[PDB]
Amino acid sequence: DTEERLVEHLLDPSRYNKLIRPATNGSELVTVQLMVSLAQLISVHEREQIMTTNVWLTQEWEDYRLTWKPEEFDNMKKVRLPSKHIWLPDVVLYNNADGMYEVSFYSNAVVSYDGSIFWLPPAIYKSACKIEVKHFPFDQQNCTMKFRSWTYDRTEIDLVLKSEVASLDDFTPSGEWDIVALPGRRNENPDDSTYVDITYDFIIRRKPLFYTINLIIPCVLITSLAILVFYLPSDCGEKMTLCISVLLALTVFLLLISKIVPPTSLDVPLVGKYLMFTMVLVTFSIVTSVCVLNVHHRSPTTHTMAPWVKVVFLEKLPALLFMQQSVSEDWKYVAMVIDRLFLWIFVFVCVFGTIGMF
Amino acid sequence: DTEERLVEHLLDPSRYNKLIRPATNGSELVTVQLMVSLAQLISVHEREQIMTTNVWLTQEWEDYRLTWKPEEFDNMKKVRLPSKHIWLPDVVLYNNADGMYEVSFYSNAVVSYDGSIFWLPPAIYKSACKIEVKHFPFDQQNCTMKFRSWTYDRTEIDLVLKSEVASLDDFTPSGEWDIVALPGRRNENPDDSTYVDITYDFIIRRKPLFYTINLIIPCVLITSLAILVFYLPSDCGEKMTLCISVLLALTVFLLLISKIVPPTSLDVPLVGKYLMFTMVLVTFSIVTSVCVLNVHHRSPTTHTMAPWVKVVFLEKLPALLFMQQSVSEDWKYVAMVIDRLFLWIFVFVCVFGTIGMF
Amino acid sequence: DTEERLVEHLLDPSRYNKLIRPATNGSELVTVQLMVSLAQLISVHEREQIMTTNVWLTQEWEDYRLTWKPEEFDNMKKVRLPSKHIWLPDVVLYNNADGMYEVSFYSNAVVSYDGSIFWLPPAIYKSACKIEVKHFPFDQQNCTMKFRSWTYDRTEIDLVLKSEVASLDDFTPSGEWDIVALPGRRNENPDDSTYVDITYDFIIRRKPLFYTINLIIPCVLITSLAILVFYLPSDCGEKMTLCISVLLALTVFLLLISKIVPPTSLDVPLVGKYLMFTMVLVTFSIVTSVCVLNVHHRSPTTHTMAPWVKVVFLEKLPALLFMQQSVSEDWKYVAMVIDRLFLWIFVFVCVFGTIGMF
Amino acid sequence: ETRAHAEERLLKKLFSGYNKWSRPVANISDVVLVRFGLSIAQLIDVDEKNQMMTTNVWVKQEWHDYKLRWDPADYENVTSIRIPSELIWRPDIVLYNNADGDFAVTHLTKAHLFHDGRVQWTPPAIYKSSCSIDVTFFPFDQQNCTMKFGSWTYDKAKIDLVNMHSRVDQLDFWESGEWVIVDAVGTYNTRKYECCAEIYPDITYAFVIRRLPLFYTINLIIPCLLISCLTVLVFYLPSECGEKITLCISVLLSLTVFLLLITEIIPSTSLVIPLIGEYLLFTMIFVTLSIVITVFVLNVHHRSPRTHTMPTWVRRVFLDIVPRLLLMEDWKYVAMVIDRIFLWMFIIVCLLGTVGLFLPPW
Amino acid sequence: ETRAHAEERLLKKLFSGYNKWSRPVANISDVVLVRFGLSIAQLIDVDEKNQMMTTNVWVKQEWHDYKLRWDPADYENVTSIRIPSELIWRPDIVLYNNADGDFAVTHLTKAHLFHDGRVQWTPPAIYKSSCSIDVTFFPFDQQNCTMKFGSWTYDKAKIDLVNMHSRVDQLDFWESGEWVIVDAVGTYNTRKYECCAEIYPDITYAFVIRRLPLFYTINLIIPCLLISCLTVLVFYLPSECGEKITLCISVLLSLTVFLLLITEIIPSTSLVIPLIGEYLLFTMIFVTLSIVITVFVLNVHHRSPRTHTMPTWVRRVFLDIVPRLLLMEDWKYVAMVIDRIFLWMFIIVCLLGTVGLFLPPW
Ligand SMILES: c1cnc2cc3c(cc2n1)[C@@H]1CNC[C@H]3C1
Ligand SMILES: c1cnc2cc3c(cc2n1)[C@@H]1CNC[C@H]3C1
């Protein structure tokens, strides 16, 4: 029964006002020791540059008008209170999307007899961290979280850390994303001198297997067919089909990968780069291949193929280590020669690019 | 402790009423000096013509019934107050989608002893700016933001600017979109004389690289194959495949680009225009190519190809600088001639259009 | 002016309390006669199993402490009141998605001098009705709507119907969906004896024309080409193209139809069934057709086609009523024979399935 | 002395014995006149697929009460004051045609008392109405969307609406870009409902609006019209090549895609059908018939005298047909012939259909 | 006299000196016993791609306080009354496993006092939990989703939960259609956290549920299984036609699409991998290898003795291979031979892989 009397004595509207803050001896600052405790990293939406987490941030401070005599009140060293009626320092994100800053539940608050207070409510937070996307999927993202009041300043409160690292004891594995470090730093401005903030910097690494399987393997597997249409004979009447199909599949994969990543024109990933390059390559291939096909399907009556071709190509034969040769047959052989030359330089350039990636 | 007495003396319900506005000496206007401070430009949704920003608009004004004697109240020159209980002039957008006008947090309000007041709450605003889309993606958009009360008029308040430019001290870079200028202008109506507004005109430029890579390069790369099917021989039996594939890819890109941009029938972008033109070109190509193919696959028994063809075409040969020619062979050569002529005029028209763009 | 006095006499906080219910002579039940009146059937979202309607549910009951003497109050037999201050029995759905139960507007309430009360507010309701999807689109859906309080039980109120049918006087036609019957039944539980509910069972029929045109016609039109590739000659080199295209279009239509309907594995519609069957058919066709093509391309040097083929096939000829037959020519004729046989059995099976649907 | 002090004294005298829920009339048989009007601000969206219409609209009401009156010479010459709409009488004005909305204003802007009991109220609102969409002449369409305002619990002998301006004001209209408002009229009406015996009034605002057709004309119909020229052409393509059915199949699948894609932009109403879907359907029909006939042809051409036979009467028939066609043992000549004769008929049919379909409208 | 009059008098006597925020116990050492339970109403959605679970659930709590007691014979024999849950004590019951939710009931249904201090509360709720999704035997999958209720600011020496029924009631369950609840158990547990020294209890409800596999079996796997028969077949297709790589490319692209489409329905967890993606991947590998080998073939066949040469040893080798194959300068015959010998190996390999992959499970 005493609890009732004690409470209804503490929160008396006449004795205790909430709209003000506890101060004495010359407007001394009230310290606010806060530390965050993660629970799980729900999601990281790249396309929108957002991160959804669940968090319990423990605040602690001191109030000089919430004290009592324990022996009077049947030796009570501790009580619960509602966190709407007592004072409390406003503390939220600043980089928040959804325009939702404050916490959700507004839990109870512990109170001792020395006046201390220890309050931790839960929260789901939608932070906005910028995605550095160059080594996709093997990337190390870096998501920031601010904390500072938005009613008071440094000349009325002073925030402090308790542990330089964000606790992780109640954390549940996330699957995709895996943490590395959770540093937390206090920050202050000398030019302003009224800007105190706490910044926690989650460092995350992605597990690559999923996107590897679903994107990379098909990608490389398909682009491995661009250096091959040259080894196909022009009598089949099929080079166009293969080349076209490859180009279209390639464009599709490109659009898709550009969908999965955000539209930040600041940096470009590696995969889209490689894909654009090999696309340019394969279109050069299609045009040179149509030229080859035309020269192959020429007849004697229509063209004479006067000197230059004869000597130039029937003498270029050995430089390739390609060998040893009715006019239509000579046409066909010229075509064979030129296509093999192009095949050589194309495989060379493919290896060159694969090196360029390292 | 004094703070309590001072506050509970100022906001006394009898001495102070909120539903009215401060006036004396003949219903004099109360000035309202407001200036906006951006924080970031969250998004620009073209398809819906919307812009999402985060903003802190600082208002300042004067009230003659919120003054006190500092020396009496322990030399207090400044206090905080809640912004629901005191007066405040209503100020919002007018072009707002979501039907949400007022601000979100309703922060505290500073108060000095001269009666001045300085109040800045935060906000996320969804403005509606019309998209001028002709030079896509190299476009300079122009998004407007209104500000005016919707309870009072000019004969009871008068809004004013403090700085002609919107502050950008806290602007965090946006990635895609890059600002150029943030002018702000006061506007008044002589015919009405009861219409005061403040209009801030953000001028934005898009960074082109992303959409460039993902749309333009494939788009030009593919359309570069429309002037080529003519150089393909009709014995391969493949012109139809290539032409059809090009046309279909083209239609796809067209539908897509029309999705990405809003459905404003007022203006048309350049890319869709070029694409429609080259589509018309390639269908003309398909029809003339089938004609060529038919004339190629004619035999002597079925047709006689009496005089006109012989002299006309075997004499047109030199005008092309194309040369030098059993009846089926003459058929095939006529086909070759006509297709080369069409190739010439088509490359000419392609260059002509590329010029037409400049 | 009297209205003021009368009201401020009835709703006096001392004389009238709202948190209790009207009772006398031994905790007698207060009857609650409710009947619903539809206005329009906004939507039926199959993919999510939801129905959105607009409804006015009229409740009526009796209260013994809201009576007066008409002649005293200037002969007033009727008044309006607000429906927050008076008592009212809680009545909502139970099968509601959105977690939104109660009504929206909370309209005024009529009051006579005998104490009766007649209250109808409006509402938009998102009910959850399970979709029986087998005769798509010619289907008769059946959407249920519950009504029961969620604070009281049968030993304190007793619900009742006024008309067994839901009124449709203010109903506006819906276009797609057309009503048939709107029965309403009271339900009670003997084992529980504290479970009173009212269930209205809307019976709906879909108008088929739209989905007919947009899905069925293309579907049947395309599948009508699966029994035809056999009548195509193997020298054209084209059977593969047609068969493949048909199979792909078929798979596309299948995925699409499975998107439009909900993912209830309880039952499977008729269209997907027919489509899967004919897909199996066409793949059997592709494999037998490649076999035919191979046997057609064979040459004399490579194979001898020793006795069995000769007699078996050149004697099977008449059983087909197919007639009358250099070795390569015999190859080609064997191919013709076998493909015609397969054509016969395939058209037979197509008719057989069309019958299987009836 | 100060205007503000007299303003307080007045405001405090008025709201001493006032009751919101009491109707403001001295004689019960007397009615109030609620002058009513609108003023658009923009037309956010018109969702055809769901048959909805979003509007941002500045409702305008004004009436007169008999208790909010005073004398101005006694209170330092104040006639107009401003008070919240949360402390006075405020009529119940609803739209019966809502769809995922709020049925009333909840912004609750202040109100202006005018010293003669007259009061004036102008709360904004975002309204989601449901208007039936008729789609036959797509995209050249004139839509007609309604909004039915009216009272809820007050008959015609207690409340009586009055339309201020017979047209909807458009002084601050914001050009949406795609839809233009031809005209917007406001009608008065009465009705009787089953609930009750008295009659209830209502007001019906009708917006007749047009669609600017450039976008769908330049992104949707031009390509479907451009790949329909290729429906009849395959016949002028020979059989030795092997690219007939390729063309035919491509065209068929493309048209099917365009139809299956436009079905996303129009509702699923079955009363009517657009004019584009029907044309595309006829085209798909004729092109699949074309693939059938051209496979028959291809089979004819590749025949051979040893394998196949029975050119018994076809000789006379086709050697008598070829002269009429003005085209002057071997099967290939007859394939050419049959191809030509079907080509003529199909060009005629496509011509005649594309024609006789679009004429009655224009 | 009237039951309602006595009911008022009682209700007015009880709430004279009551304090919500005061714990209802006479001796500080004494604890209250919060009997707890659930009752499903439906299982709205289980989002695999985001790893979430939505439930509509009728929480059930009951306890006993020492101030809400009276005598019934003095108040006309009333024992049970009903009051809002907004004026009495109401314990803090939270789920630590939320994801885009509310952490507590926001509907605040009334409460039933039972004349002996006992009080009973049953507020509904929509809860969004996050349960890890294991996907290997897709679609034949048994999922296991959790919900961890418990108190926030009350230790075990002030509050102590008690599970009413060891199973989750399903009397008003609404069959969702796709997911069925095999079983649903409720465990009690304790723990100690870093914040503090005392121990805190908790309750853990586990739902083990199954998926009805007809839909994805009918619409997703049957076609990917039906276009895998065509992976090995191209080899039985000759080289004079020109339709080998066409078939191969079509199959490859189709399988790639099906994989790139199923990646939309499963999460992006990397711990495990489904059994369908892996099979499709192996198939794509072998079919691109097939296109490589068949282009090599096509090159061999179309060779010629003048252009190309060096059939030095291949004569003996292939004329010695052809008899073992039971198949009796010829660029054509050696092409046929090599084609056949690769066909046999690839049918063997596809057989063996499709087999040895699915066996350990069954
Ligand atoms: C008393 C209280 N509410 C009513 C609501 C309505 C009616 C009569 C009422 N009478 C009908 C007429 N106006 C809206 C509906 C329907
Ligand atoms: C003060 C007030 N409430 C608390 C709630 C909790 C804790 C500490 C608290 N301290 C953690 C330990 N028990 C439940 C959670 C988590």
Image (tube, coloured by chain):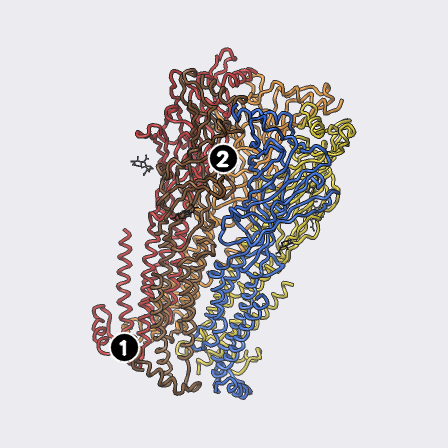
Chain colours: A red, B brown, C yellow, D blue, E orange
- At horizontal 39% and vertical 87% (from top left) the residue drawn is B307
Q: On the image, numbered disc 1 is attached to which residue?
A: A330
Q: Quadrant of residue D279?
A: bottom right
User: Nearer the viewer's eye, disc 2 or disc 1?
Assistant: 2
Q: Nearer the viewer, residue E359 or B279?
A: B279
Residue E305 in the image, given as x and y percentages of width and height? 29, 76
Residue B210 in the image, given as x and y percentages of width and height? 36, 51
Q: CA distance from mark 2 to mark 1?
A: 97 Å
The residue tagged with tag 2: helix, strand or loop?
Answer: loop
Q: Is residue A216 visible?
A: no
Q: Quadrant of residue E77?
A: top right
Residue A231, compared with residue B257, is above or below; it is below
- Specify whether D41 is left or right of D271: left
The residue tagged with tag 1: helix, strand or loop?
Answer: helix
Instruction: Confirm or deny contact between disc 2 and disc 1 (CB under 8 A).
Output: no
- Specify whether A213 is left or right of E168: left
Residue B157, compared with residue E66, is above or below; it is below
Q: Is residue A355 visible?
A: yes
Q: On the image, numbered disc 2 is attached to which residue?
A: B155
Residue D259 in the image, given as x and y percentages of width and height? 53, 62
Quarter of the image with the C terminus of chain C is bottom right
Instruction: Name which residue type carries label 1.
Output: Asp
| Mark 1 crowdedness (10 Å alpha carbons): few <14, some 14-19, many ≥20 | some
Quarter of the image with the N terminus of chain C is top right
Circle count? 2
| Mark 2 crowdedness (10 Å alpha carbons): few <14, some 14-19, many ≥20 | few
- Specify whether A157 is left or right of D65: left
